[PDB]
Amino acid sequence: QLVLTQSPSASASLGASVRLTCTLSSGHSSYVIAWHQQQSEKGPRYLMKVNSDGSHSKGDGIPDRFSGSSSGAERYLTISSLQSEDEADYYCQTWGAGILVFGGGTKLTVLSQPKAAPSVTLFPPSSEELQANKATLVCLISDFYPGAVTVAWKADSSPVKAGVETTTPSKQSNNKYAASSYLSLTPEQWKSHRSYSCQVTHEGSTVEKTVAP
Amino acid sequence: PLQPEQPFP
Amino acid sequence: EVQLLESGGGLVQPGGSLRLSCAASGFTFSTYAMSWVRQAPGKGLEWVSGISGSGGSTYYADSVKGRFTTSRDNSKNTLYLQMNSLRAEDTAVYYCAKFSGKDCSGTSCRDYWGQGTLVTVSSASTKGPSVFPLAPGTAALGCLVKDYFPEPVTVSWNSGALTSGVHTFPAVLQSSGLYSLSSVVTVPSSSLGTQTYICNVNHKPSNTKVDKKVEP
Image (tube, rainbow over the protein chains, first blue to last red):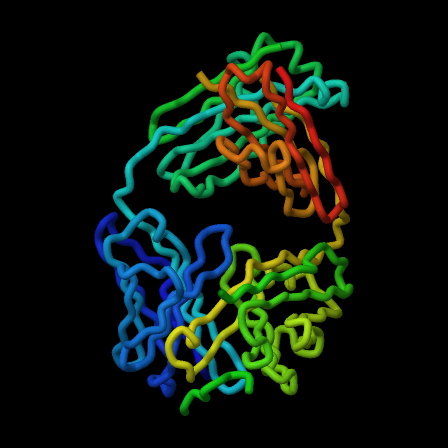
């Protein structure tokens, strides 16, 4: 059966080069494959085709940094001078009789990127939502790298865990990460305490913002 | 085998 | 150049039906076979179907055979995918795509993708969002888009006139099963009394369109 084998992940350093490998199952060693790039929350982008003599048919605007090559049943995509934007999922794809076949995709991580402290904005419940007999605290976290944070909410000083919903960080167009945390309260609790706080912790350092009625 | 020119002729 | 634009995605009950369209432009539609590819959340690309340039031959992955149908109209330059007997695991973004094969031999050997459209197969029903303002050298203000299902929600500011400083955050999926997101804009602290700020929230699955004014 026609199968394409890709490792799930790959990594290399900023400014360095990386080689991604797609292997055809035995008996299809002469087949043409295509490389497709998919950045997070985007649709795929065709890069090029690679047959046994290497060769290409690069898509529009594909950088020279991107190139393809071939050896036996293996097909390669090489990206030199890696940039943050090169972090993506890379799929190889081929076809047979009346079928298309995709590899499982390889997630490329570009190492050695600059650390960035999170920017944090904290909003209190809107007036309109309090006359709707609800109350939401909104903590917006952006421009941080790497993409991992822990959030801590405090009713004054006592920490509060109930009513917390927090996203997984995702990479924004500025190539830094964003996330947000929501604290649900009764309008009673919002008015009872002298303040509430959102503490974001990123690489051992904590940024805190606070709001009060 | 050999791959056809086109998967969906 | 080539353009492929999907439409018709949305929320469907299990066992229900839905038809997707793909409007194509920039090439002679009938000279190329057209494909459907889908992607379940957090999973890889999965081939769904292909159809010959003439429309004379259709091809399906086993995962959809006997339930999905593909067709095309070579005067409207449109590709179709008709889904019946939908299942929860058919939930995915569905991409329209054009794969060239071996001819071609330069730029004609390129492949092309559409933008995708989201199909949700679930017994959960639609819910429109409630929208709340977020007040107040620069100031930050935004809109809270609370308790909706399913994705997506679009947010603009002043009907497209305000684009710089705008950051619309990814939605949180609450344990209730409903989404919430926020869209924030950074503005000079001087135009706060001069400039008017309205967020335009639109949630197509529920026909919800909200314009919310944000004041200090």
